[PDB]
Image 1: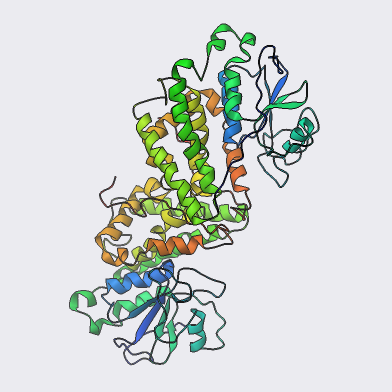
Image 2 (image 1 turned 180 degrees about the horizontal axis):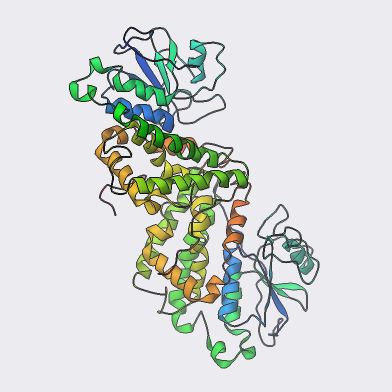
Length: 300
Length: 293
């Protein structure tokens, strides 16, 4: 074999009036790692939707261990944080509190319910969609109206998401975790084919769909912002770089980062690089490269 | 302790078909001697055997031991590894079994295994066998020697060797202490080569050859494998990049001796650094065309 096969997510519940998980302020909490593109999706949207005082956040240590994601008191790292609520030591401890028999993966992000002490949802694609509407009664009308998956654009969003997810978001991982030459090449080639395609899409455009920010942008962004800083080297995704091989992706990427604080404030390059280059099975020296300089170039 | 020369009346008389280079295409050190062999028109005067780029626990294997396209078997002694040659010259040799080897087939010994000396041998030792345009070439001429020495000193320590100091560092502190002066030296070179074709004296010299063998491997291997990645040549250093592309594309000595598959295969086969042993498909291309901007 040699190819990476991502395991789907198992906690797949929603936050709905009159449902199992009623919308409430101060009840739900996100556990995340800044290094995770998946978890960062939820940080971005939480800020886009003005949810910072409605949904809590805890930043786990980026130093993924044999026990999984440690909390910040266990593996200190600047900006990492201790678990506020259960004296958990590793994210696994949250899952096994929700269900001591759980045998999925102990992934971030976790959208947690502090009332019943369980995982509402650990699928980042669903969490950000929960955020479009579930907490709207707690928001001003104009912030409530924000929606990154609007009905008029949904079919175009879904169409781009499908291959972006398969060949780019997961593609970097299929390339980087490959353990045979053949599996690596079978992942890296479609990755860059999809980047070539995105480049044409973003030529002369500020957003992927409808000339406005959508979740398609958020989902692509979290991969591309990590690309030159970590994927190119650590994961060998190196046919070309964003900054010198893809000027339309590069301009789209820099406008989002420099002009929308939801994208820069949730972007911790030290967390990102520390995480990937701590992966012993790929980088046994554990050295963290000093470049690229800069992590992201200015918007000029 | 193999630091001998080829001189008329010396221990090793200049002769056609007598001296042989054992090299790996991946080695910058060995590739210096391939470049100068082509520069001086010595291809049919001094032979070459290409060892496998797949460095092993026994060192450099020959192409029949570890096959790779273009890697050859040893034509003279059925050697399996380069060490076998050294130990033929001296069964007690306890140095490193490095390429390049400048070998004398007559007495079966190592003449010289210092690349910086081999290429200087090549400037004159075989001139009687050369046409006049090739005999006249000298890459370490007296009028430029002091400047060539000056540049060579820091290029050798911080650039030629520096990629290795960074890449084989095992502590963050050691890696940083090597990669920073490396890029400081590239910054310096960038200044030297702005508006210039050559490092020293508006003519090709060994200074160019000794730098080229590192810079040509930079984007294809040192950036990723050795984490020499503050910036790239092609995106970070336009004056170096132009000088590199001019030498590669305008001078067959530099391109025909440059086998990117050997280069990448050797470095990414280093399991201590790259345990998956996977070889990246990029960067594409290995070197950009001369008229690229």
